[PDB]
Length: 292
Length: 284
Figure 1 (cartoon, rainbow over the protein chains, first blue to last red):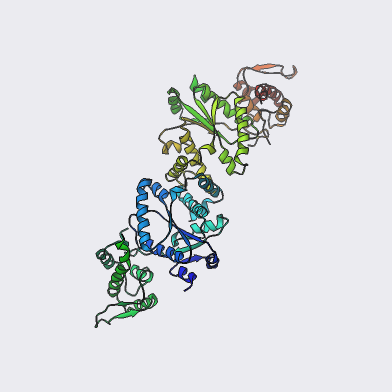
Figure 2 (tube, rainbow over the protein chains, first blue to last red):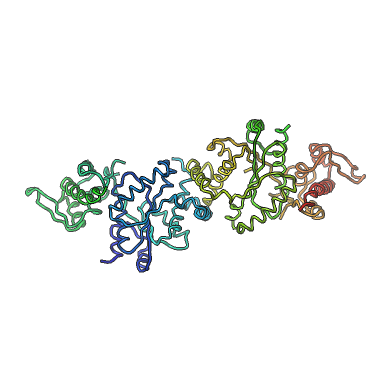
């Protein structure tokens, strides 16, 4: 088995694998990830929750921070109106198999002790170090220090997130006494190859087939290919690609690796791959769609 | 006339027109924020006199004691800073000020207030402001201070607040007081309101004060901002003898023509300055 390997699987980067190994040995450890409540939960989200579940299976206590305060300022609904969406999100994640504690940013991000720390942090952060991570607003340089403060406040051992905010985690290590292990998940490529290019975990078998069919997917090309990415990150192996007895016949790959190879040497054509991943994804998301 | 009284000895009044309007209202308020200071010098006293004008002009006065700001700049714990602050209050009352005092820490970490700091930062640019992040935040906290205290007038020094006159519903009138030059002419170089007569005379003597030069002359600045006229300036009968100036403009005239020598000016400024500060020092 190995908990380290399970946590590491399908991650872009783990900022200090050696620290994680030390953290895994602790009798008590915790990890968190932030999400702005969202009406639709797509595969990007699901990818990350699967990671939290890996950590959950390794003995970590999970904390999901629901960024309602930020959602309020970005001008989404009212606090109580966002809470409804948040609780919905809570249902989805629970359906995904996550067992976590949920905290709404508004519960603590306006507290005096927390606000006082933002100002302290700001006195030690350069406008450069902060802008790092068409007309710039002040909020942009504040946001990353609030995030560092969240890491301090929630007391976690591990902070999880996409590869995008990987520089926001450089500040934490720089500005807080306790060093936290950062875990970064890959960023999924939009269905078109680049807002309607997402597959929702609760989309219908019809919609999924539809969204998949029109999807970007050059034969031979794997990098930046949304369909391949799905197969690498959600599909179970081995899996068999149903095939015309004349078109080459059934293919039985036992790993994403093999699949990748077949796709590169063009043994497997775009269409044949799409139908496989499509019906395959549909089964994998099925158990979640029901409880929703 | 109240508009003139308020304009008196000010660098600039951002929209006299707006001020003129404010004065019409039956109720109006103005504030200035100070970071508690161990020693109150002529600089502070100059601004308090301005607050006193507004006071006499019917403005309710608010003194914002910047303790939180002090605290964040490692200037000591808060309770210790309130001690210095409470003192400053006594000195401003001894100067004749009648206002309500408020410590920043009492509201600057409140939810409503902090939530308002985040809204403002979402509409302010990282340019129309600006090196540490805090630098670009203070200007937003200030606009928020003006908003929170709900003042019609904000007094301060020459230091981007009409920025507030843009992202705020109520327009505020800004007033910027001139900044004093040091005794040596460059910016432990200042007279304190509570200084002893003998110390004042000492500080005056060594001060930068070129015969005929008025620009940047601290002795002339003291003459223009605190002395009263007609001013009586004694002088040995062999140096022109005693002369009585009825306005600051005449003083400039005399001094600029070397008709008034630095020594004689100093003795008059020092002796008069002393007689003015006394009623205060005689209360602390």
